Image (cartoon, coloured by chain):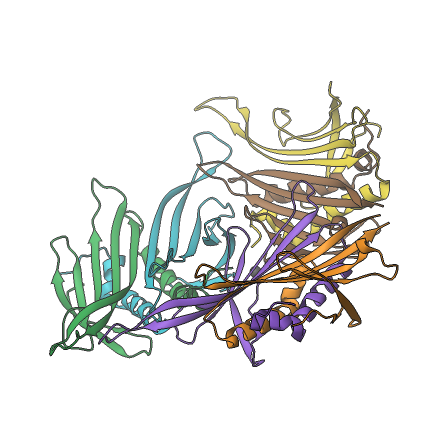
Chain colours: A orange, B purple, C brown, D yellow, E cyan, F green
């Protein structure tokens, strides 16, 4: 996946174009979606970094961050989503594919989505 | 959300029913789906725990875990019965840090952005195929 | 009383629907009524927790909290009502029934209600 | 509110007249209703005390107490006269923490919410029947 | 098993409704049925608690308790009011030890064996009649 | 209860005959049903023991055990003969504590309550399915 701008749909299904911002010192890839006025403090961000195993480690650590700030009219507070997948090296790609599919379907399920959107506990 | 068995789609978009197992001492709620064998030793799990803020803490910390174990059936040499062992596990661990001062609109499109990022092929190759961005 | 959303009337007699939020580690039940914009800091809350007696204690401690925040336009200040009933185990339910009825009628009485609403001392 | 005897309804919605007894050194105002016997040793009481804030304290602390004693008539073996003893007491103790910066609308619907919570059957079973939420 | 009032049949086959009381800090779930008097001092109880295995120890420890208290209403000499007291209690305490690798079939017919043993007249007189086997 | 082979129904409602094995030195009575193989190494067992009260302590301690072993036939490498081995065991252990002053009615409806609890689907899934109550 060569670094390239990616389009994501918001709650209204409207397209939202994140352009690539930065490749980190550690390997983190930062995509930014600026606001209308081009205010950095208001820009959405998406981070993607994958950590390979070392010293005969079985695990892969792949991280995806989605940060949505809201500006307060000067200082802004940020809602964040932070996902870490832990993937063993022997697992065939079938497993990782349906694991992702499971996560996305859990986000789509109304009961689970209520947990995040309405900050309600399970009871 | 009243604890209820929830249905999630796998890679083949087939249904996969997770039944509620337990509500933890810490507030963690566990849904399980048993393996192929009727034995429960390794099982697909979904954990949900939301941590409310303290001392007017700005932050709710809401966590979602999806654990997919691969189990292996070990049967000793020339034995009648076999025992099941947890071979390895794939995991996905999500922590949303939400501020108590935000509007639900923001959380809704944060979740939507995360789901669309998972659906995007360029980002999906990151997880599935373990390719770095370059 | 299985955990379930409950409806309460505000000062204007308008219905106000508290949905169940959380069952605590200690047993506290939290119901939340979000605002129009779904701001947590603005949500009304109602807590209910009952503490059984132990080590041959005669008393039951049943607690009801009603927290009403008002948002200041970012940080919000909360008016609270905190009720603790102390109920012995030998008392027949008749007593607890008319004790509650007494409390509610005291809240309804204009003289006593002035005490809370207008923060006036008795004189 | 000028101290006046107030009438409250019991479980049977019958009237119960509390006459003012005393205004305390601390500002506590006491209304009493005597027991069945003409003897005052145990009696239904309603206490009201509001504590104004200090050093521009944000908070008024307004307290309402409703004490319901059950008395027992003990008469010694083979005795002419009986003495009354306080057997046990049920109590309800309410502290409203109100900020000095709020509007009366907020306090009005806080009180209304509390009264409607007391009227709700699910919440009323909590007090009357000592059932936990689950 | 979502928490629900469960109806159990007594010796006369009459129904006896146990309402859910509380979910413990340790995971214990309590169902209660109050005594003849409305006073909730001694009450018929059913406790259920399952203990997961630690460090993949084969055992699941699933426990079921049925406590039947016999209560006594004692009113002292020359006293107006009576108080209630727990006279004695009959108890049944069941612990199933279930290995984490047996499939559900084994646990099903274990439960069936236990229930049929309770139903058998010879085994029943052991409990009911306090007779030894001989 | 004279010692007699007792028939118990399994999950499929098929009969399972337990023949009396032994009366212990401590009063324990054992009924056994042999495994599929004729080899009496691991065997389904039902233990019954009632303990009288000491110094008129109110308690009678009446115990019922149902042990279901799962066996494995292991034949070593390059060996003519196979030997059998106890792989694991599911167990149900019941202790009734019965006060020496309650009449038989109380014990009868206690047993009925326990059997109906075992029959209830919600309580049953607790044991069979190793699900917590929630
Ligand atoms: Ca529930």
Does F11 appear above or below A88? below
Answer with left or right where residue C59 lies relative to residue B76. right
Does B39 appear above or below E82? below
Displayed-image quarter of ligand 1: bottom right
Tell me if residue B72 can be seen: yes
Tell me if residue A105 can be seen: no
- Give F41 or C54, whichever is nearer the viewer: F41
Residue C20: give x, y in percent of width and height: 65, 56
Identify the image quadrant of residue F34.
Answer: bottom left
Identify the image quadrant of residue C64.
Answer: top right
Toward the top, the furthest residue is: D25
Identify the image quadrant of residue B38.
Answer: bottom left
Residue E15: give x, y in percent of width and height: 45, 64
Toward the right, the furthest residue is: A37
Considering the image in quadrants, where does the N terminus of chain F appear? bottom left
Does F13 appear above or below F60? below
- Give F111 or B11, whichever is nearer the viewer: B11
Q: Residue at x 38, y 52 (%)?
A: E68
Answer with left or right where residue D88 lies relative to residue F87. right
Residue E86: give x, y in percent of width and height: 40, 42
Q: Residue at x 77, y 32 (%)?
A: D59
Residue E96: give x, y in percent of width and height: 33, 60
**Number of numbered discs present?**
0
């Amino acid at each position: 996946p060569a670094l390239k701008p990616i389009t994501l749909t918001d709650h209204s299904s409207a397209d939202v174009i994140f352009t690539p911002t930065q490749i980190d010192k550690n390997g983190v890839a930062y995509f930014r979606h600026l606001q209308a006025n081009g205010k950095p403090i208001g820009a959405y961000t998406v981070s993607s970094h994958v950590k390979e195993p070392g010293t005969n480690g079985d695990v892969f650590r792949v991280k995806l961050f989605v940060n949505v700030p809201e500006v307060a009219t000067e200082i802004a507070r940020t809602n964040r989503a932070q996902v870490e997948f832990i993937l063993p090296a022997q697992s065939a790609a079938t497993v990782r594919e349906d694991l992702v599919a499971l996560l996305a379907s859990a986000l789509a399920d109304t009961a689970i989505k209520s947990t995040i959107v309405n900050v309600e506990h399970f009871y």
